[PDB]
Image (cartoon, rainbow, N blue to C red; front, top):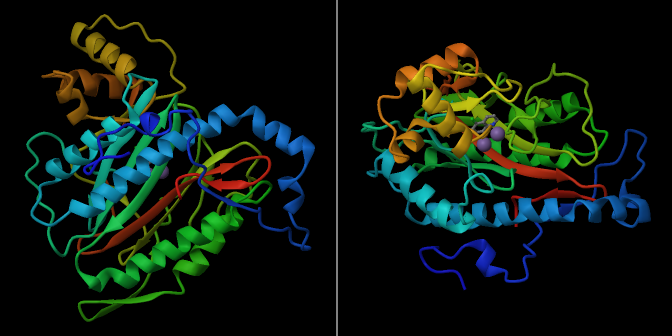
Amino acid sequence: VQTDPPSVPICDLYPNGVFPKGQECEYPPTQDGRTAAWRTTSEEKKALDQASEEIWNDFREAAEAHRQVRKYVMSWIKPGMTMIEICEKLEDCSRKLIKENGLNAGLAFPTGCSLNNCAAHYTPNAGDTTVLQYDDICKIDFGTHISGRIIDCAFTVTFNPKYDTLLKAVKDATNTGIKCAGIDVRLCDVGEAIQEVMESYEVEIDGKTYQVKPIRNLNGHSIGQYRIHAGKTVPIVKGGEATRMEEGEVYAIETFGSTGKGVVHDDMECSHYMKNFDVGHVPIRLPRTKHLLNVINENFGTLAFCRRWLDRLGESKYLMALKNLCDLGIVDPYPPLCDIKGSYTAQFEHTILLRPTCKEVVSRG
Ligand SMILES: Oc1ccc(Cl)c2cccnc12
Ligand SMILES: [Mn+2]
Ligand SMILES: [Mn+2]
């Protein structure tokens, strides 16, 4: 059985190596009204699904580690704790349950804990003294992987009930997107359903009223092996590309709500970095720059990492070497994305598998 606090890896909790399936759903029907129910019992669809079973089973192990980590996080996350303490307590648990093993099993990306106006990509770097406050709105976004099969899943943490309707708007739009998603469904269609649900909500925060806005330049995306964003974007506003979702694909269905401008800009010190997937081998002679890239290739490959994870490996005075990799185009920085000062942003995100037989919300129990 799992301990309190959790320390037993998911692998050890299922000796047979069969992890629990997430929520399974029938696909949404067409414009004329034809059901997708036929997929659930088709010989040809069941065959293709069973062929990728070892893969679905990898996302399930990673998803079960994510569920047990976020239930544990919800039990102790309180104002007064620093952002370093939150991330380290979360990551230590994540490492134990995923049974971290180099590139074969581990953390798929750094622990986002973005606050207030900052919607995404904020994790503390060393020496960051930020402390979580009672009126803060914190987005916990973390990832787990087994053999590069990534679970991208996020939720918003608040202590003041004044943000309840803001969270409810975004949660409902994320559920809408998950519901609309499916094989042959246009990506712009999923984006318009999300916007329609989010804008139906009106919030009052400290005597001020707002209609919840989707963050138009933030969006859902496709997931590939060892690739967080595989190229297909799921918009959260009207206007997006009429490109369609295909069979066997994996999507992260995230939506963002804001009381601000509904658009985000790079701000603050960067913590998130990721090697560019399309960049091949680049011989480097600069010794410190060479060393840092070998550290990246060994420990992260093409998965995102943060500076705290470099400090953790015993690395120091690597900022110039890291800047060199960024300017060379080998590494891309992913700085914090903020809306305007004084605005509030919320996020909810699940991972969905577009299986031949059904739609599996693998990150939801
Ligand atoms: O949900 C996420 C968290 C962190 C990062 Cl760096 C991401 C990059 C691309 C897409 N989604 C992401
Ligand atoms: Mn995420
Ligand atoms: Mn994501």
